[PDB]
Image (cartoon, coloured by chain):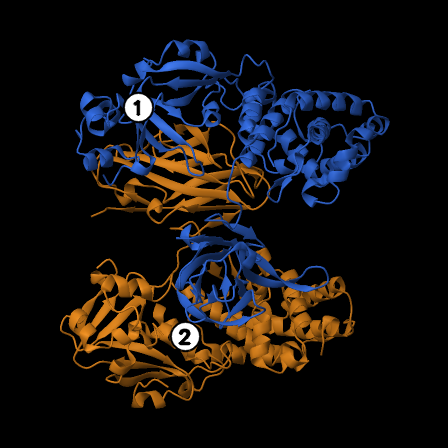
Chain colours: A blue, B orange
């Protein structure tokens, strides 16, 4: 009983779920669910068709191969979803008193097990969380009981007749109706067109002729590529790319050039003539954010027109850098296909719901510091009661000793005050009390009463204590900021003195 | 019951503990503990070195004088009541005290001493002293505390040493380790400053000084030159040798430190040691002066520490005319204040602390951040046949950086990688893995779809281990004590390698 979350268990009629299917098995699987020729051996499905589709790619070519499809499988009649709180077979069988020999999924398909936990249903399906960061479940079915499932087709990616994995990824992008929902046929065509025509452009032909066109050093291949990147960017095909990449130093020509040098150095002949091997090699390079226009938590390049421009620019740069630092046409063929595949992976990551830095236990990384709420409950300021709470914040830095100057805390007249007594900061166990003064009616600032430094080997725990004088709940009208502000070292941003700001974002909730 | 930790509670005869004491009370307090709301009480600790932390001039807490540490003993029998939570309201409920009477009034009554003292003549509350500390704090009811006898452990002021040196030399005893003589370091510093400013090339280089306000780039350029020259004098000879390779100790950082010092020290500030300390304590870059980098205190001999501080004193003096607001500071309060910050950081590094990638301390490297999700995750338990799971958090600070794979320990029998349950999830997208042994002690798992992390994209790497033998695992059987998560591919000494993100585990039995 300590192992079953009944809150997530239920019986249902015509229980449905989804199963990703690999190329070839799409039509065969509609015949019926059959085990092919250990405690957890069973048929696996999920409640999220979009997460199912990720199980659907050619296993001989998982990175770049073709995507099969998704089938929906339904049990006729009544089905008991038994949600389990732990994924250790031994543990389960004990706290349920099962045959510590019989495999767990062996036992789950027996009349006896179906009797005990079935609640009147014809069979049991186990439910576990799909993954960390996911709200989906994975369903584990017994292979005998699975003989009863009807199999309808949800989608077959092969039928859609699109290039690469475009079908699978445009499917997954439906999950978000924000949302990067790009037409990759449009982007592929625009890309081809822009490459072809940029090649025929006068200043580009001109700038190519100036190329050492032979093996050289990274330092000068990089210099040339930076020059090629500047002139290329001046042509009308790349006018919008020029405008969106002029400010953010992540998108500068020097990073395009470093990318291009790095691709050209690692792509041999064996590699270039295979999409799977190409993708694997490219997938371990740093700096891809430069080409994607992804930085600071945002996909900036989010229109078909600007993505194809960026990919076209990058395709030419690889072409130029290959004779300078390489070893061989790939720049227009396998390179473009592989990099489109990588765009799709990363766009999909950003489409999926996720906590930003400084939310829940996701670290906030800035100026060499790393700061985070110690547990999920710490990031929650409970409301609607008279009294006290504590909130732990972890704090360190990557290398040398960097200071912590203090922390800015939210206050709300009557409902949220800084317990100045219990608020402190502890550095490798050394407990440091704080002097807290109010700035205005909504912000208190606490400073350590002896110096705080963190670094490699030196971490701090910032303990914030809140007091509530009323039991009236906080309403949104009442609170401006949603972050606690830990202040690092003092710097001069904009001819003016400021502290590095390490932000930890809280949620106001009731019990 | 649910609120009291029997295991850390006990009755003791002549229970003693320690109390830090401010200047002007080291003698007063020995006459007796008198009071001069829930937690209103007298505070002591089982750790006399932590107690020494509370001994500093409350009006000058950064830099003021340290008072002393006294030992306080109850005669007869005393109950130490250790509590699992620190919320007064929770306590009173789960123990059935009155929700009106404050906790530290309740605990000093015969009704509480009857019910909770196990026969002792009074109760003391024990709570954990701080995160990252093994000490406890004791909360003594004030009236009961009248029975305490008070003996002197140490009076820092009678040592008659400069600054806070007596306090910090006492604290350094905890590790029998950085145990420097600051009297010696002060004297060597005075001496080296005095003889350096009379050296020929130093006087020569001081003539070349603009000796007027100039640009920050200009003064930086000048100070780097002064640094090179000074470092060639024989007073700094060993310093020259130790700061030659590591770029954190380069002259450009000394230069940057001195520039930033001069820019924040105005006249009010230079004339007050507490204000100078306040201002210096929030500057970046001090680790260059302290010789502190990569988790280690490099300058750990009195001669080298004096050399670095002497050098910095001179540079501060040269830098003030070029970006300043005032020059006796560089040898008066600057050296006093910086000696103090030295002592703080040294003390941090003397205290036991988990290093990056140990337990839940993050490993920060090449823009990534990785950590064991929980303390238990970092533990590979042994002594049974079966399975365990281990979660590792992964992200990066800005652009998408890849995760190539992970290297995992194996042992022919006592430990194999469970390739079914081992996986990696990226903002919820579950990614199966291809694992291939690399010898008999190291398996390498690759993601079957590309993995990138970055601002707003994180991964959970789930490692599943299988044990075939109940036989425990022995120290010899296991080569590495770390799990290797591989970042992007880079070149180091003409060879390709992945960024290495290390998570250090401990092997243990269970109970």
Query: Between tags 1 and 2, which lies in front?
Result: 1
Label 1's element? strand
Evaluate if marks 1 and 2 touch, with contact meaning CB atoms under 8 Å apart: no
Please give the chain letter of the residue carrying mark 1: A
Provide residue A111's location: percent of width, then percent of height: 19, 21
Classify 10 Å Cα crowding around label 2: few (below 14), some (14-19), many (20 and above).
Answer: many
Q: Is residue A426 visible?
A: no
Question: Which residue is most to the front?
Answer: A472
**Quadrant of the rendered structure where residue B412 is?**
top left
State which quadrant residue B244 falls in.
bottom right
- Pick whichever, B167 or B235, lies toward us: B167
Front one among A279 and A207:
A279
**Mark 1, other Cα within 10 Å: few <14 / some 14–19 / many ≥20:** many
Q: Tell me the number on the disc at residue A79.
A: 1
Residue A330 position within the rendered picture, expressed as x and y whole percent measured from the top left: 66, 21
Q: Is residue B248 left or right of residue B415?
A: right
- Residue nearest the observer in this picture, A448 or B36: B36
Residue B346: percent from left, percent from top: 46, 67
> According to the image, label 2 marks what residue?
B53
Horizontal side of residue B507 vs A489, given as left or right: left
Chain letter for mark 2, please.
B
Q: CA distance from mark 1 to mark 2?
A: 64 Å
State whether discs 1 and 2 lie on one chain: no
Q: Is residue B485 above or below residue B177?
A: above
Secondary structure category for the residue under label 2:
helix
The quadrant of the image that shows the N terminus of chain B is bottom left
Does any portion of residue A337 appear in the rendered image? yes
């Amino acid at each position: 009983d300590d192992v079953v979350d009944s809150s997530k268990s239920f019986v249902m009629e015509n229980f449905s779920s989804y199963h990703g299917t690999k190329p070839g098995y799409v039509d065969s699987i509609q015949k019926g669910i059959q085990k092919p020729k250990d405690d957890w051996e069973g048929f696996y499905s999920t409640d999220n068709k979009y997460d199912a589709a990720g199980y659907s790619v050619d296993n001989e070519n998982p990175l770049s191969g073709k995507a099969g499809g998704v089938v929906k499988v339904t049990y006729p009649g009544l089905t008991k979803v038994l949600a389990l709180k732990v994924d250790n077979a031994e543990t389960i069988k004990k706290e349920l008193g099962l045959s510590l020999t019989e495999p767990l999924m062996e036992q789950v398909g027996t009349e006896e097990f179906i009797k005990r936990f079935g609640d009147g249903a014809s069979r049991v399906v186990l439910s576990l969380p799909f993954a960390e960061g996911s709200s989906s479940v994975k369903y584990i079915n017994n292979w005998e009981q699975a003989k009863a499932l009807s199999v309808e087709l949800e989608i077959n990616f092969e039928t859609r007749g699109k290039r690469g994995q475009d079908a699978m990824y445009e499917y997954m992008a439906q999950a978000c109706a924000s949302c990067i929902n790009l037409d990759w046929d449009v982007i592929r065509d625009k890309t081809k067109t822009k490459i072809e025509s940029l090649k025929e452009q006068g200043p580009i032909k001109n700038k190519m002729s100036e190329s050492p066109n032979k093996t050289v050093s990274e330092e000068k291949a990089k210099q040339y590529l930076e020059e090629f990147h500047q002139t290329a960017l001046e042509q009308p095909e790349l006018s919008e790319l020029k405008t969106v990449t002029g400010t953010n130093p992540v998108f500068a020509g020097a990073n395009y050039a470093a990318w291009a040098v790095n691709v050209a150095q690692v792509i041999d002949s064996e590699t270039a003539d295979n999409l799977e091997k190409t993708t694997a090699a490219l997938s371990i390079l740093p700096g891809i954010g430069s080409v994607m226009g992804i930085a600071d938590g945002a996909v900036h390049h989010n229109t078909e027109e600007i993505v194809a421009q960026s990919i076209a620019l990058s395709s030419l740069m690889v072409a130029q850098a290959i004779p300078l630092v390489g070893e061989l046409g790939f720049a227009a063929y396998n390179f473009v296909e592989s990099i489109i595949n990588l765009f799709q992976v990363v766009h999909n990551s950003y489409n999926r719901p996720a906590y930003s830095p400084g939310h829940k236990t996701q670290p906030f990384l800035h100026d060499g510091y790393a700061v985070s709420w110690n547990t999920v409950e710490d990031s929650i300021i409970r409301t609607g009661f008279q009294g006290e709470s504590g909130h732990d914040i972890k704090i360190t830095a990557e290398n040398t000793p960097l200071p912590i100057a203090g922390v800015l805390l939210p206050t709300i007249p009557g409902k949220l005050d800084v317990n100045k007594s219990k608020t402190h900061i502890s550095v490798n166990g050394r407990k440091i009390r704080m002097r807290c003064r109010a700035i205005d009616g909504d912000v208190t600032f606490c400073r350590p009463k002896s110096p705080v430094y963190v670094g490699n080997g030196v971490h701090a725990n910032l303990h914030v204590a809140f007091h509530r004088s009323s039991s009236e709940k906080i309403h949104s009208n009442e609170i401006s900021s949603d972050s606690i502000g830990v202040l690092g070292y003092q710097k001069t941003v904009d001819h003016t003195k400021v502290n590095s700001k390490l932000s930890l974002f809280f949620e106001i909730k009731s019990m």
